[PDB]
Amino acid sequence: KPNYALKFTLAGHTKAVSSVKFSPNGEWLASSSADKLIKIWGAYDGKFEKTISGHKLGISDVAWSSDSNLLVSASDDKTLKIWDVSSGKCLKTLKGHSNYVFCCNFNPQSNLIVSGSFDESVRIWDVKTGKCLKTLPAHSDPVSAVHFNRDGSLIVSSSYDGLCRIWDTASGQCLKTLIDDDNPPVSFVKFSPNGKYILAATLDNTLKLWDYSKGKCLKTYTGHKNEKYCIFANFSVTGGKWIVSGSEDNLVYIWNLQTKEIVQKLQGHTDVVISTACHPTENIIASAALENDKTIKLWKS
Image 1 (spheres, rainbow, N blue to C red):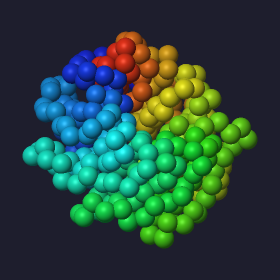
Image 2 (image 1 turned 90 degrees about the vertical axis):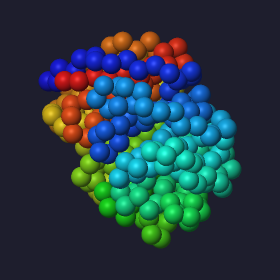
Image 3 (image 1 turned 180 degrees about the horizontal axis):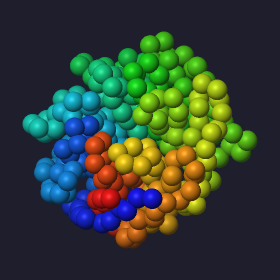
């Protein structure tokens, strides 16, 4: 079992936090919020660094480039924006989604950005020119999450239409469609660090680990509350191999990845823990919560 303990509580966001992400170099924590702002914090002391602004409506997601120099954010303003973190500049504003953009990620090469939206599409963008390379008619409902695999050859996406789909990044073809017996909306999905699995969350209080090549559900993680919101889940691999997730009962849940047993619950948030993140080299978890909390918390084992 892990021994995560509260260290820092981080405030500033004037509205509900939507997403928190550690920089790949482990130096920083970026956060986005319905308050239209991005904030940078020291990953180890939670020391506030800077605010990044420009979006005209709330942000639902933010993600780092591989080299920890860039950010992409996804806003209800129907744009993504590429930020240079150190200068604070908006480098590109990506436009073409017809509805709120909900989710984003760079590929590991960070020449491409993938995005998903309420306009039910998945779009691939060129980082250098900021132009939309492909629009995938990916789903029949809002796209809750999008993620590249370890080499960027694949995209996984999830949607309120109950599906999880794997896409060929080069051709844009659907290579797979995953759904279990019940068709609850899929609220989140991401590739495992080695990229052989996908972790996916459904609005039926369930996380599942899938081997997407075989189309098979390997593990199920239950015990948390997730029926209304797109809560991030994570693989934790710095110490034990855990699954980490926020919950609509204001707790952060940690399961043993292999045995599926809850090993720790983190208390202290006063609203839905919408987002959690795992530090790339230390046993640190960042957690953020919604409107009645507005705080980010940093835990260490």
